[PDB]
Length: 127
Ligand SMILES: Cc1[nH]c(-c2cccc(N)c2)c2c1C(=O)CCCC2
Image 1 (cartoon, rainbow, N blue to C red):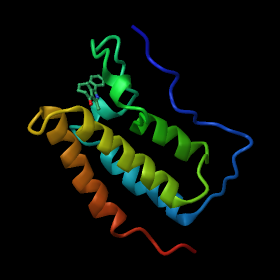
Image 2: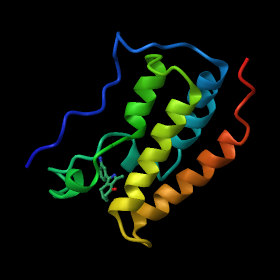
Image 3: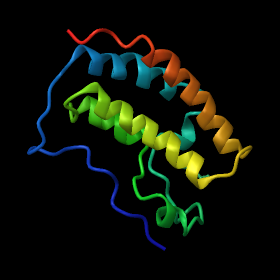
């Protein structure tokens, strides 16, 4: 069994900028979710080999995790906040696609997503 290569966190050909919204996403949003008790399944890519999930990457074609997001934010990978928000929503969506309602992992994603939504509600004005 085989995992795919993880999502890229560096791309010198990709335009990039530092914005106050992106710093908020690192310093407030990512920090809030990273320290949560339910964060650990989401801090790195899903290892479908060790987890014995050979169908994971057959179903999930856009994997995403907070470890990748953290490195992308720290490496200034993004152009705008929307790109980073999309990555967060992709990671939650993957969890809901692959798992059953009521699975513990879904309850964990749900709790993180609630905090995510509470924090992005106060995303500062782009300035
Ligand atoms: C998001 C997610 N994370 C992890 C996991 C579990 C233990 C260790 C590591 N690194 C990752 C899983 C998962 C799923 O969606 C499928 C359900 C269980 C596996």
